[PDB]
Length: 195
Length: 195
Image (tube, rainbow over all chains, first blue to last red; front, top):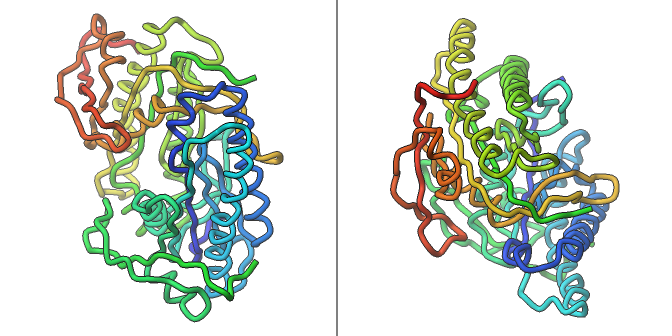
């Protein structure tokens, strides 16, 4: 049964991937995307996230449902997962460069925390447990605004993580579907990161 | 096994839905979204489309795989499906208005035709048969650019459907990930529509 719950919601994609998909053999592309998605899946499991879906190279993970550590630990877990994924991308790039893939590929991420609706949604032979709401769309918009290599979070997320994860103010951006400007921050790796 | 194939790719979403998701009881929201997705699914089956996935109220359908009618009939089928969905939305709105949902809700759609990579993509316990590529992203971008109630298509799609479906030039738009401007058209219902 569908509920309204405070979640931290994470989106990511690989900048450079679409270009890569127009020049790799289909089999090498399949293996590179699936390797990536499998490695990202393992990191999301480690950090306690709920993997929602993949849309090509786009990954959506949420924290706070079906279980929760409370809003602060859920947010710390989501951002720490992103820190960890960005570090693991360096490893994957080294592996890829060894297969002769040279074109640059970099993860970007958007994270927001707020109340979301969670439930089973879909058509009768095509149902999924997933989330919807403005706060879900705000995570997606942060991801769209982020630069290669950047993890962008909203002020609500920052408020939760600021004593334990190092951030830097990146101003306020124009987000379509958002009249008012939303405060954003970059997440910066530091000595006390959880991993 | 993964292949490169000429597909027509369709995306849609409901303008107004995100606002609605922030004010409807979760159970009424669930029933309204699932009714919508089930009705859209039935129309895509009727027209021969392959339903890829739903992402909240966003629907993705493609034509040309696993089977094909040839590039022209695949494109005519995808646009005719969109015409039909836009007509059925009038019915759904009348039903919704009778439950006291008054806020405006309107479908928008983007359609493009071109070579795409199709295959099984994902992590080991989370695999899906789906499509990727620049031409898939161009359909998504047309959908993002479309206005409520509009079906926007690219020139490649228009080239295929122009003798049987009535269109109007809507200029060229700025599409992120696209340097050059892409030619776009609105699809206009007319007497000879297939349904």
